[PDB]
Image (tube, rainbow, N blue to C red):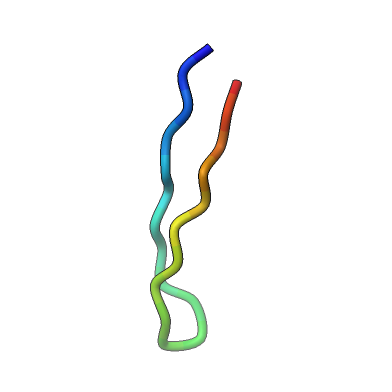
Amino acid sequence: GFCWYVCVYRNGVRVCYRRCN
């Protein structure tokens, strides 16, 4: 399928998570 990155705020930080479905 198609993958994508999800960035969010956590502990005063912003990390992106590459999810694939």
